[PDB]
Image (cartoon, rainbow over the protein chains, first blue to last red):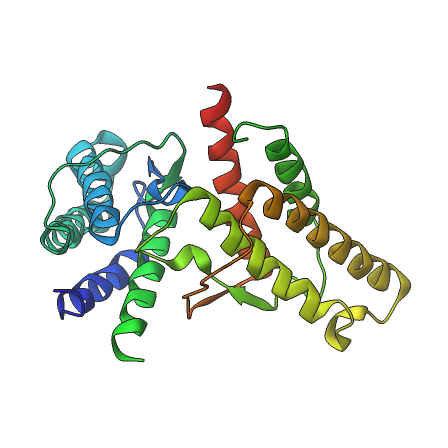
Length: 129
Length: 129
């Protein structure tokens, strides 16, 4: 399923994420989009599904992110809800639960999310345009 | 030749470009790094060698870029010298002069150059680290 509405779910969720801030949206993930050797779409997804999943699992109850105020704690609570959802969809479209994250370079969650939001919208374009 | 000094030539030139401005560094190229399906390293290069080459050839004597003042015209003159050089190296490492630029989305020359500068530095890391 390649031009499935799951793409819209991914984009629609990407927007929420990209339009928010936290002390955690600056911590780094593996830049799987720093590769020159490349792969295949479903593996592009399993790899991305992987890094996103390593993050939220590593940062769900992280001290640097839980927050001082209420609006902050709320924000982080929301940040992790979305990561889980964005990831839930990625694994489904990837349909591949094994991943060789061969990369050294790290982006920031936020800058990585933009690139995912971009790749996804290009993937969408090819579905309608 | 994969960990050749040509990589340093590419990075070293990428730095000059990325650390400069022009009225032309905002005009758009094809975002070949918006693909999810992916390819192979030498094809990643032929594709990049292609877009860069379409640009300078399309913008060498472009009115929006030639410049009003002297420092401006000089800058554009320099912008195109580097594009030719960065491209000269890419074709050599790509060793492949045929390219299927299947992409719709466009980045800006400047934002595309950053990503190339990044991919290149990751490619370098794997050569020494």
